[PDB]
Image (cartoon, rainbow, N blue to C red; front, top):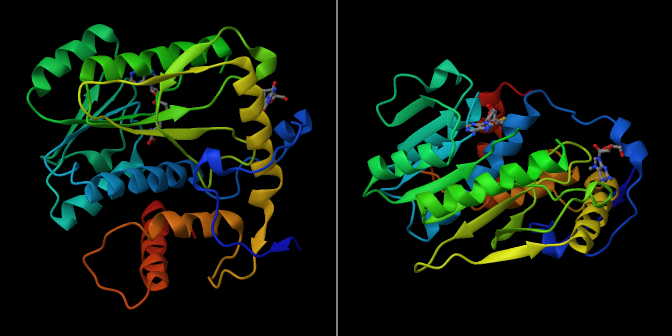
Length: 291
Ligand SMILES: Nc1ncnc2c1ncn2[C@@H]1O[C@H](CSCC[C@H](N)C(=O)O)[C@@H](O)[C@H]1O
Ligand SMILES: C[n+]1cn([C@@H]2O[C@H](CO)[C@@H](O)[C@H]2O)c2nc(N)[nH]c(=O)c21
C-alpha cells in the first residue's frame, strides 16, 4: 500500500512543490473510479468557491450566471444548500443543451437554452441590471485552438458581465501543442479532488475590486511547468493513503475533500469539524447516487 502522513493537502496550484516529466502512457490509464465523478468534482469546487463569497458577504443578493451549466444535476444540490441557509440568490443557467429536469419549477432558477456569444452577453447584462453578478463558467467546445477560443470567450464574459466574482474552467495547453501566448484573469488556482486521474484542469477563482481587471500572460514555459506540476500531483500525490487522517476513507482525494468541506456553513451545529464533514460528504454522495 502507498502510505504517508500529511499536515494538509495542496489546495492551490502554487503550493505544488515538485514535478515529474509527463508520461504519455498515462493517457491510457483508468480516468475515473466513481459514478457521476464529474458532477462530484464540480459540486465540491463550486461549494468551496460560493462558501468563500458568503464569508466575504458577497453572495447574498447576487445572481449567479452559470454558462455551460447542462446537465447541471449537481447544481440542484448547491441551490438547495444556500436556499436552506436563508441566503437569497437567483440562478440563471445557460447552455445550448438541456438541463436535468430536477432544476425545473424553482422560481429562483431560470434555465436558458442558448449558446452564448458576445452579443447575447450584452443583452443579458442589460436585463440583469442592476443586480450584482457572480460568474461560473464550465463551457467546453480539445485542440489548443479550441481552448484558446474558450478562454477568449471567458474573458469576454468577465468584461461584458462585469461580475463581483468568478470561477472559470482552466487547463493550460500542453507545450507540445503550443500555438501562441494568451492572457487569463488573475485569481487563485483551486485544485480539484475527484478530477479525472491525469487531468491538468483546475478552477480559476477571482474576486473583483474597484473597476480593475488584472490579467496574466501565459507562456509556453508556463505550459511546461503546468504539465510537470500537474503530472507530479496526479501520478504521485493523489495516489497516497494519508494514514494519519482518521476518516472512513484515507485516500488523498478524500483528505483534500475534507479540507474543502470544512469551510462550508451548516444550520445544524456539530461537536467536531469531522462530524460536519462526514455529514456533508454523506449528504453529497446520497444526492448524486454515489455509494
Ligand atoms: N457558448 C456556449 N454557451 C453555453 N454553453 C456552452 C457554450 N459552448 C459550450 N457550452 C456547453 O459547455 C458544456 C460543457 S459540459 C458542462 C457540465 C455542467 N457544468 C454540469 O454541471 O453538468 C456543454 O453542455 C456545452 O453545451
Ligand atoms: C494530461 N495530459 C493529457 N494529454 C493528452 O494525452 C495524449 C497522449 O500523451 C495527448 O495526445 C493529449 O491529448 C497530454 N498531452 C501532453 N503533451 N501533456 C499532458 O500533461 C497531457
